[PDB]
Image (tube, rainbow, N blue to C red; front, side, top):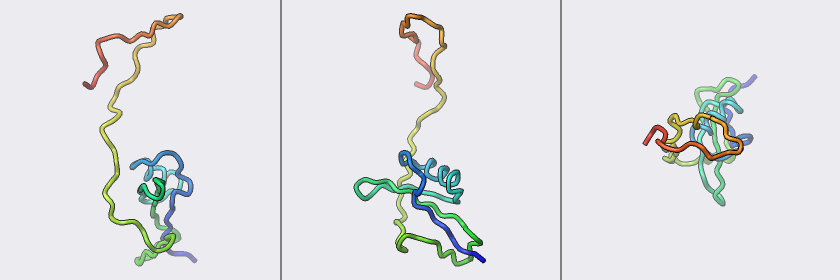
Length: 108
């Protein structure tokens, strides 16, 4: 009938290599359970995700490439970015005069 684990190797991830993006994209594209990213081989970033398929027995026994997954690793980059900082109020010049000017936006 069916009962095992299915893992994807960025077979449809595309785009840059991120942390949450790799996982989200995995569950959004491959509807997996958990995904991760790793840079290696000519600097090529690969995304590996694992999700229960068919039934997923208590033994797991996924479908790896060669039965040799990556180490525990410890990367997952995600610096402090994007914290609420929209563009200025579109006044309208025509011709354009740059616009903006001080004071500066929020978040020092």
